[PDB]
Amino acid sequence: LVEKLVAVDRVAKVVKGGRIFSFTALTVVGDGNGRVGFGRGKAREVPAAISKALEAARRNMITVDLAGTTLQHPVNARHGASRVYMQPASEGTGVIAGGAMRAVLEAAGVHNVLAKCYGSTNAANVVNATFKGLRDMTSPEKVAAKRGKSVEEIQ
RNA sequence: UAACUGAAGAGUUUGAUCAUGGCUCAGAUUGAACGCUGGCGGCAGGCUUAACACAUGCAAGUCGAGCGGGGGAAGGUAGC
Ligand SMILES: NCCC[C@H](N)CC(=O)NCCC[C@H](N)CC(=O)NCCC[C@H](N)CC(=O)N[C@@H]1[C@H](O)[C@@H](OC(N)=O)[C@@H](CO)O[C@H]1NC1=N[C@@H]2C(=O)NC[C@@H](O)[C@H]2N1
């Protein structure tokens, strides 16, 4: 299980006499062969925040059906004001994406992809959109099963 | 055989936050200019502004097998 730390931020809460500071961490875990998840953690210190984020990421996982080491088809997804577009690429291309998309894709095991963000680039929302797109991407076997055809018929 | 295959973001409004939205940055390119410095070769390029005014030299001649004249050099014969 490879673990990646997308972002760490300091947040404040106002009380009488001053401010209480805390830290938030966003993490993505993945096996690298089709299983990936993400989570967030809040704590008064960075190590505890990262630990909580990793535990939440392990509790929130999905399974992704890749075509080799790339996507099955182009994907459009969005969460809130963040929109993402991902497209399969040939061998040797690599992962052409921003940091937030790159964490999720590398954790899921995608090796060749072209990706783009439109709208807001907030890390949590971008991770949400990429996660949803990867979850909703389909495969020829599922398409054939749902249509009642064969894979060769589907083409 | 081959004639293409292609898309990354970041900073900044607030005590935190998300969104909106400008401004700024990372790239490629140039008939460039300026500052510091400067060994060689190959191949290119070189008034983007005053279609402003121009000294001087050169950048369109050739034909005597179209024609009549006119020149000045070599020869020969005759006298001395
Ligand atoms: N919001 C607070 C509302 C407060 C409001 N005052 C309440 C009120 O007044 N009346 C109550 C009326 C409630 C209404 N009838 C039901 C309703 O809201 N239906 C719509 C919401 C569906 C559902 N409920 C929420 C949901 O499934 N979220 C998931 C979730 O976050 C996460 O997936 C998981 N599994 O964790 C993520 C992937 O990471 O995908 C999100 N999905 C999505 N993201 C996308 C996005 O944004 N756009 C486009 C599309 O793609 C979206 N789908």
Image (tube, grey):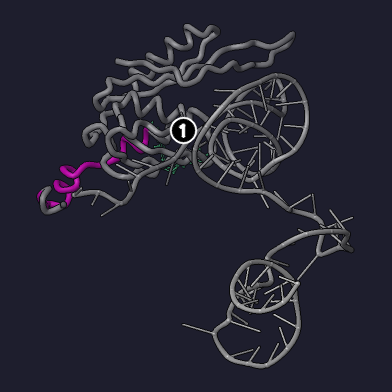
Q: Considering only vertical position in the picture, is A86 above or below B62?
A: above
Of the four image quadrants, the one with ligand 1 is: top left
Question: What secondary structure prevails in the magenta region?
Answer: helix
Instruction: Answer with the quarter of the image where residue B7 lies.
Output: top left
Question: Would the CB of label 1 be found within 8 Å of ligand 1?
Answer: no
Decide which of B71, B25 is in the foreground and name it: B71
* Residue A27 shown left or right of residue A35 in the figure: right
Decide which of A95, A92 is in the foreground and name it: A92
Q: Position of residue A22 (x, y in %)?
A: 58, 12
* Residue B74 shown left or right of residue A43 in the figure: right
* Residue A69 shown left or right of residue A127 in the figure: left
Q: Residue at x 42, y 36 (%)?
A: A129
Q: Position of residue A127 (x, y in %)?
A: 43, 30
| Secondary-structure class at tag 1 | helix
In what quadrant of the picture does the N terminus of chain A appear?
top left
Q: Position of residue A59 (x, y in %)?
A: 33, 19
Q: Say few, some or many: other residues with alpha carbon within 10 Å of mark 1 (under 14 / 14 to 19 / 20 or more).
A: many
Q: Chain of mark 1?
A: A
Decide which of A110, A59 is in the foreground and name it: A110
- State the extent of the magenta-drawn residues as a range: A131-150
Q: Residue at x 68, y 16 (%)?
A: A14
Residue to which mark 1 is pinned = A126
Instruction: Answer with the quarter of the image where residue A132 lies.
Output: top left
Does the magenta run of residues contain A70? no
Instruction: Identify the amino acid type marked 1.
Output: Val
Decide which of B6, A56 is in the foreground and name it: B6
Q: Position of residue A88 (x, y in %)?
A: 31, 40
Does the magenta run of residues contain A145? yes
Instruction: Answer with the quarter of the image where residue B64 lies.
Output: bottom right
Q: Considering only vertical position in the picture, is B26 above or below B28?
A: above
